[PDB]
Length: 113
Ligand SMILES: [Zn+2]
Ligand SMILES: [Zn+2]
Ligand SMILES: [Zn+2]
Image (cartoon, rainbow, N blue to C red; front, side, top):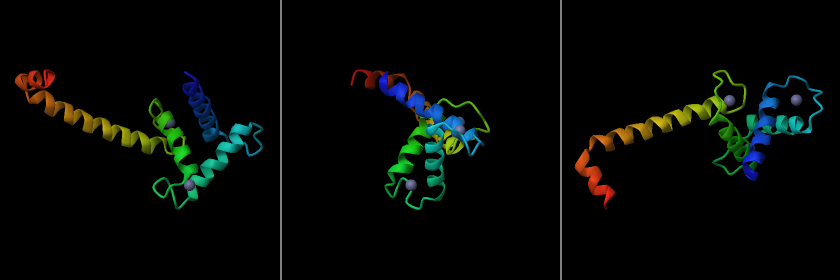
């Protein structure tokens, strides 16, 4: 539960930052989040080049995106991560369909394998 609450707080910070138009915003979590998001906009390394700042922000956005129900969400990376998660769900569904279609005798064999 501890890490879940930590993630929850950080998601709250990201959600606020994403919709905050006050350059004079006094919330330190907002100021910090805006700097991190600005970094990700220009970074050439990104996650595959090993950038810890990008990896941390995208991981946070992914935890947000998993539960996000907003079609025009302003959170950085949210829409794009939801697209990736939808594709993964489709692939999982296609796999499951093929497995169910393989039939009773197959499933029974596997169950007792
Ligand atoms: Zn703010
Ligand atoms: Zn980066
Ligand atoms: Zn979102």
